[PDB]
Image (cartoon, coloured by chain):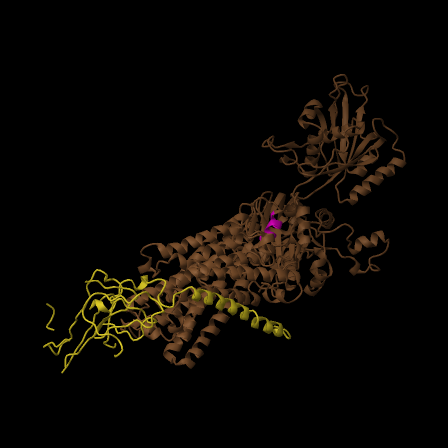
Chain colours: A brown, B yellow
Amino acid sequence: LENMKKEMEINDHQLSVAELEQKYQTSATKGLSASLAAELLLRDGPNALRPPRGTPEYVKFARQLAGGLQCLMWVAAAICLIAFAIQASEGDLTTDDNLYLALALIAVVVVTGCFGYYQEFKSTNIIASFKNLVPQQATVIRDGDKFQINADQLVVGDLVEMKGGDRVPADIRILQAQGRKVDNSSLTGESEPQTRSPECTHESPLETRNIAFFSTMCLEGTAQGLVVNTGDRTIIGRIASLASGVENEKTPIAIEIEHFVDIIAGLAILFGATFFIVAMCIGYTFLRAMVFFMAIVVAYVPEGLLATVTVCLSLTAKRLASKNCVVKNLEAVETLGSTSVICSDKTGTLTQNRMTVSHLWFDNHIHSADTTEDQSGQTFDQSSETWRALCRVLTLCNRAAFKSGQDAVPVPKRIVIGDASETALLKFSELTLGNAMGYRERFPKVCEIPFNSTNKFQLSIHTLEDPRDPRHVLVMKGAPERVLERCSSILIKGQELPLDEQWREAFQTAYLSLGGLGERVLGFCQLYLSEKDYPPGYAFDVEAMNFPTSGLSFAGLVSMIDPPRATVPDAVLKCRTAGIRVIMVTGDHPITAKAIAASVGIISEGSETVEDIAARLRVPVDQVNRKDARACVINGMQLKDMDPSELVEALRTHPEMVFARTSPQQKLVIVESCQRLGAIVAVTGDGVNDSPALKKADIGVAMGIAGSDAAKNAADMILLDDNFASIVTGVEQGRLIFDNLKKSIAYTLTKNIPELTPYLIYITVSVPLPLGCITILFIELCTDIFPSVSLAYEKAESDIMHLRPRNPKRDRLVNEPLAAYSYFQIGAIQSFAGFTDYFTAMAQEGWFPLLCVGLRPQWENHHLQDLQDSYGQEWTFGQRLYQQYTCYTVFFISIEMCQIADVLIRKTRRLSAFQQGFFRNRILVIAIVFQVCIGCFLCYCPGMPNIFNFMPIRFQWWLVPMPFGLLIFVYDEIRKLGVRCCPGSWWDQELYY
Amino acid sequence: RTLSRWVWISLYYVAFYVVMSGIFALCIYVLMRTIDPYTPDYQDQLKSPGVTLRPDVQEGSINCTSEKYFFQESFLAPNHTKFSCKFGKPCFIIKMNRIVKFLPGNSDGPPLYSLHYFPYYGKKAQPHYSNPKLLNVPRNRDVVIVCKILAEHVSFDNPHDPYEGKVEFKLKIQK
């Protein structure tokens, strides 16, 4: 399905024209016959993209109700429902119990579902911003008369004609043109117009002059070419089919949770059935034994839990929204904390996407301007005579002009009508020199000979401002070797001097060096036209040379380059420290790509590829060993040729890599290669070129402003800000939470034990039920909720950025050691704290504990009005029931009291409460108070005895569990201490979360 | 999965669950020490007495007469055992739920307590204390009869304990 597209394309571009004609069965001049055009559509079928199959049915909502977890609550709700049904064999009470519970359950599925769904109901939308980029009609030649037709009609074979300002409708073989230039950013990610011509320039079809591609727009000129490729056949539409209908897949957090439900269902079920077989020894039949199995669901399943994790995720997410980091998906909050490798697009992602000057050579010395946006470097030289006379030519011999739109924004930043080179010069001179308009004003421009392709140099004659002269100055610029041929002298400092042979090299010398940088080089010279040959008035003759072209005064050289946003190089190095690998992936050429890699730190100083080594080392390329060359840079042309098992090895082999001149599929290939590796990749990209990649990445981040519509739809996240830094913050926002979530799990789960044990003791001991199903819902739904959520505020026990990425399979979110801790140890202290309160309330009433055993059948027996307590007093049904209802309420409180300790303990895994401070978390302290106040309400406030069977407690009753809460604080406090400092052994490797 | 150490997990739980059950007993046994052998700390639950009947769903002692409360003394161990008093259309014996130091006070439907017993001393203080006829000419129908006790000390709770100072039952003699 998806594979074939991964390979590069294979072409026809140095087929001859007639030949092409005879393949397609088409006429060059006259074009397809209307007849033949139609027949060729039905065979091929339109020139259009297939309705983004994957049409997520609004019904999706329902994907949320299910999941795995919601499934444990549905099973559970449905188990409650079946038990109520099974009751129905008699006369039963479940009218308040079992049906209420199974409702509380499904209601917790539904609700949590709707929350999640809502929040999620904000992001989707890709194929929508992708076909916000489609021409409409086109002008085909058929029979031999042309005619703009609906695009979709176009086929393979037909003659098409494109002029400046159109979209190429389909892939096309250029038969005829001229001056036609095209924009091929869609393929390269690079906007500078490329020339089309009827001869094949090169082997690579992506490279030849003769093919023009769909998803591209003809920039200027005019041209005709034969449709090689229509619809989803074109180079691009392959790239198309290769994305949207991409499959999102599970997150890690989502996976850790489904693992969690796996350990949970694993105990719930194994105690639930074990409560069957024990039951059955005792003297319960199939009837009763079955009842308890399913009864054993609620104690086990934290109802509690789904909503806490979401609130916790939600809460973290609105700290990040404040960070100017938006998050579309709740699950995304964690992810970040796993990203191994980042595949980043260069242009507009890493880089500002712009251009500028670099340095000048004048005065025989190489000069390094400042290329940075908000210009953080140093002013290189203002003093020289040489410099101004250079500054003069740069401002005058220049046709460019800044847009009105602008005086507000800074000079680097404002848009300029003209070619890239001349805008550079204008900005340079605008920034160091003063207003350019001032200068041009001043030295009015008499006559000028525009930059020909021929001359390869542009000149102007200006009347000099110095009023005392207003004579004529000649300024020129253009190919460095063409300027020189052009000179007799050099302005070295202030004076001229004889372009000896020595300065012919020095120059020669600067030229070659600045070339190397991968910088564009221009040459500048000028001439003080002798007044006594050119009278004040004189005609010049841009026509033919009535003035001197030769023996001029070589002024100096200017070059240029390109830099990246500001935060990037830093943003890069944090990541590596994070121990993530960064990989550049660009459409752009290799000199540039590498220079940036070196700037940002993807490539680290004297890291080396094999071709750098060959240089210093003076040696070939072979007798270099590839191994030595940590770094790599691989040009797409070479990438095409390799098998995916040669890609994988490059990928192991090098720690700093640069894939340049890559096509979109290739960007796609790389990302897949990295994933075969089983590494989590983030693709960071701005363009339509980056679409498949982005679509392919575990997480696709798009620059908000710059980013094509296409990358944005493709992407999971968007850096509104363009702020690359945000990517580091994004990676951190997915660790802390991870740990704090375990604390809240440990916290919640602990309570489960004090909740289960009463029921079991009930069936085993034959005592009056200590704690009721309604009581339980107050603890999970109510009291536990603030304190659980409360954990998300907890800080770092250690500098988290310091440790390596978690190995996903090895270190789960919920592991045995949490269960043990929660169930086996802490919990269990809580249970006793609970049971204590039960004996105290009954004992006080007259029912001593010894007499309690085997009572339940008399105590539950509705007909004995008579029940004799230890003292001898007789209690009615109702009166002994109020007493048991009071216990239920006390037990409920016990747990909260014990939960206070559990809260404090759960605030730290390793660290004592003392180093941490259990203190600075304000949210947690609010949970202790907003959970006691709840308890006290359920107990105190009238109505509560009838509605929720909660009875008022005496002051004494509160303090029963207090020895139990204290012991928990202490017990854990001691355990950690003892962890901290045997870090290798036993406490740590059983209890440490 | 410990392939050794289980051992380090066994010695552990045996002298830590151990430790935890010897603290828990610790607190039960403190709590039990602060309660009277003879009377409960809170009588409140039992506050108004209920009425219950036998209808399953003496020598020693002292001859008495219908009279005023017979106080026995304090609720204390140093007088031996506090001396108690004596006493085809089915028979239903009603009785008033004991409660320690309580003094009850006193000084047409289809066809169909003597103070001297109180206070009740409570079982430690009085082992064999004994606490204190629908001849109807309708057979062949299910009658409902509510019997109830009156007094200042006695309250009913229509909404709750229907037992509280009353009964509700449904005889039936089919002959």
Residue A779 pos. (x, y %): 43, 60
Q: Relative to residue A348, is residue A501 drawn left or right?
A: right
- Between residues A393 and A173, which one lies in front from this camera angle? A393
What secondary structure is the magenta-colored segment mainly? helix
In the image, residue A666 lies at what x, y percent? 65, 57
Count of numbered marks: 0
Q: Residue at x 84, y 37 (%)?
A: A507
In which quadrant will I find the C terminus of chain A? bottom right
Q: Looking at the rendering, which quadrant does residue A471 occupy? A: top right
Whether residue A694 appears in this view of the structure is yes
Residue at the farthest bottom position = B175
Q: Nearer the viewer, residue A631 or A973?
A: A973
Q: Residue at x 9, y 77 (%)?
A: B137
- Residue A555: x percent and y percent? 80, 31
Image check: A575 left or right of A298? Answer: right
Which quadrant of the figure contains the N terminus of chain A? bottom right
Foreground residue among A41 and B6: B6
User: In this rendering, would A795 be left or right of A944?
Assistant: right
Part of the protein shown in magenta: A726-733
Dividing the picture into quadrants, the one containing residue B175 is bottom left
Q: Magenta span has A232?
A: no
Q: Quadrant of residue A723?
A: top right
Q: Is residue A701 left or right of residue A302?
A: right
- Vertical placement of residue A380 versus A834, above or below: above
The answer, for residue A123, to whether it is visible in the render is no
Residue A976: x, y in percent?
Answer: 60, 60
In the picture as drawn, the residue positioned furthest to the front comes out as B79
Instruction: Say above or below: A66 vs A723.
Output: below
Q: Nearer the viewer, residue A782 or A652?
A: A782
